[PDB]
Amino acid sequence: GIFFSGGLACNLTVNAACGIATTGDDCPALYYPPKCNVQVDPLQMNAVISEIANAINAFGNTYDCSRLDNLKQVLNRARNICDLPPFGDAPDMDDRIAGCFDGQSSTVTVQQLVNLVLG
Amino acid sequence: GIFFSGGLACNLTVNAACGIATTGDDCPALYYPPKCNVQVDPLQMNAVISEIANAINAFGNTYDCSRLDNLKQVLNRARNICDLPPFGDAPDMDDRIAGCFDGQSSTVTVQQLVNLVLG
Amino acid sequence: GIFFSGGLACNLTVNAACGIATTGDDCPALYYPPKCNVQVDPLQMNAVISEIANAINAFGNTYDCSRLDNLKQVLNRARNICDLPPFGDAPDMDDRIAGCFDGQSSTVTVQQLVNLVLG
Amino acid sequence: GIFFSGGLACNLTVNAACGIATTGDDCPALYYPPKCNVQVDPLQMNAVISEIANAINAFGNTYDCSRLDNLKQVLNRARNICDLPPFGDAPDMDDRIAGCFDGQSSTVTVQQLVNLVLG
Amino acid sequence: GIFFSGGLACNLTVNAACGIATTGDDCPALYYPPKCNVQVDPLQMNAVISEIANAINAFGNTYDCSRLDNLKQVLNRARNICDLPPFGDAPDMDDRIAGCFDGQSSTVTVQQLVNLVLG
Amino acid sequence: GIFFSGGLACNLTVNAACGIATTGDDCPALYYPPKCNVQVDPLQMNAVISEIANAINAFGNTYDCSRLDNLKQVLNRARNICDLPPFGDAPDMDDRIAGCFDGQSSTVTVQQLVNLVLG
Amino acid sequence: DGLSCATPAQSRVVEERVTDFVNRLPPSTNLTIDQLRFIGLQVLGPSFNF
């Protein structure tokens, strides 16, 4: 993947953060050694570029290199609620509604809210 | 941008994801070729560095080089509802509320909310 | 960090974001100069790989090297609300409810909604 | 002396300790970089030997080459209040007595305990 | 920890105090072997100097790089019960007072003191 | 011991503390020289490890490898009274009690305090 | 890594030589990266990525 297959572990180099949960040993977390002669692999830069690009094209947005801050816009559209499309239908039985309940962000049902507002 | 200037298409190389949406026939989707004497372009790497840096500075946060998870904290603050600051005033009849609706995550206006609860 | 150590300022190269907010002179924003006798520093690349790895690992997701849209799915799960876990405890009076307010992505306490719905 | 002259900062190394309160700015909490072929400076070891020797020499004790628990003995002498010298003459009313009052180790005036016992 | 990773057992070397109590076999106590081709691990020296730094900041005192007696000063402050903070409120029966009883440093409550003196 | 076997006098090098009390000249205090290169002796580092580890295990505590503040905890255990265990029997007239007297960390026996109470 | 850029003869002889070197390494001696890298350099040339 984005990891150099002929690489090392975290404690065997620098600027490498281990503890990377992976879907098995076949895609191990390996990094470049701290030598002055090794060269960055192009067929890894491809994977990093693919990651960033697939991130940018999320939500239907389109990439554009005239703006070096595309991922910033994607993050903003990911957090800002307003960006969400208005619910084009009348509300109903238990359409869950989100919020920082008791400290943890989670969702509650409609009936759970009417239970407290009826009281 | 972040793509290689004289690269190839998606299917002529490896670790190259296509379906990338770009604006116009310029700024195309070109990745590194699988050849022996191709090295990663510094100017092209500057684009990736700038994209990551601008992704870090979302939400006004500042980037520190000592830690290797700034993007993780930014992406956490994205989903952490509790992050959202309190609203400076009282709501009204037209404001929208976040929430899911039959697998159609959206917003609901206080109008239909009060209409359903008043019944 | 992810910036090139021996690099130049943003305005002295190409594809270099300007105005990146660091956390002090300690971590300066420097990019690869437009010269020829310069190669991508493997350690600087380790930094970027680690950043993307942490971003993928966020939200309890695991990395897969067979897919090139991991960060994209992480962003989608960040935006989607039904991905948020359901809540079991009864919402006390002082919870938070999120939604649009005067064109702003914020939240209000349950007090505001109940006092409005009284009317 | 300690805090190796050409060292890095808190997170840039391994096993570093953070938060180090230092008089002035020219005495930075530095740590050996974790790279290839770095050797610890003799002078630093000289400073650490000086610190440990002064700590052992404290309380008027002397150092022994045949014993490897001198600092432990000095720490024991710091505790075990029975090593403190007796008071030569009769005490006065404004003296202070040590005790752990309401879960915090403090001192109280003799007048207070006399008023308490007379009650 | 501050021990050497690939060191030897307690009695297989010199200048080793063994019987060291550690939490868990996972991190044993291993000392540098007596081989002429071994170099001290700079990470281990980082751990040692980090321990000394954490110790030197105790009691609120800050570290000074110029002067070299600091651990002696902290130890003196430890055996300086005169430097203890005076109590603001009045002690009660449930409070504790320390002294040398039957030769051992221990504590007793003020209630025992008044019971003894009233007899 | 923790000194350098083939070192020089304190005044001849830097970062060296002079006046260190030792049991005779057979255990001299010597330091690494600033002149022609010398590598730190691994056995001397073993001695320092031994000293620190013995200091940690005092007061019945055990060494931890996950964190790096152990000596700070030990120094907190010193100078903190009530940690001192309570006395099983009743305070006899002969025993001594602690307390700062005339600005001196001295002790006084129960006879004098009982006489002050009765007087 | 990087051995697929060379002709099959060079790849085969480099693998044979590195196997031979590691198998004949005396006890109590470090297996450094520089030695394997020299074995590869002496066959592939000095401007080869390996």
Image: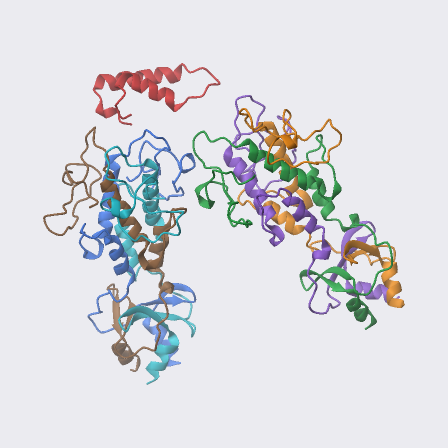
Chain colours: A blue, B brown, C cyan, D green, E purple, F orange, G red
What residue sits 33% from the left and 49% below the top? Answer: C55
Q: In which quarter of the image is residue F34?
A: top right
Q: Total number of numbered labels?
A: 0
Q: Position of residue C50 (x, y in %)?
A: 35, 43
Quarter holding the N terminus of chain E is: top right
The answer to whether residue D95 is seen in the rendering is: yes
What residue sits 72% from the left and 35% below the top? Answer: D63
From the viewer's side, name the closer residue of A27 and F66: F66
Question: Outermost residue toward the front?
Answer: F11
Q: Tell me if E46 is positioned left or right of D49 in this view.
A: left
Q: In which quarter of the image is residue D110?
A: bottom right
What residue sits 57% from the left and 32% below the top? Answer: E30
Q: Quadrant of residue A106?
A: bottom left
Q: Position of residue E49 (x, y in %)?
A: 56, 40
* F17 relative to B107, above or below: above
Q: Tell me if B26 is positioned left or right of F71 in this view.
A: left
Q: Where is residue F10 in the image (x, y as percent from the top left)?
A: 65, 32
The answer to whether residue E20 is seen in the rendering is: no
Question: Outermost residue toward the bottom?
Answer: C119
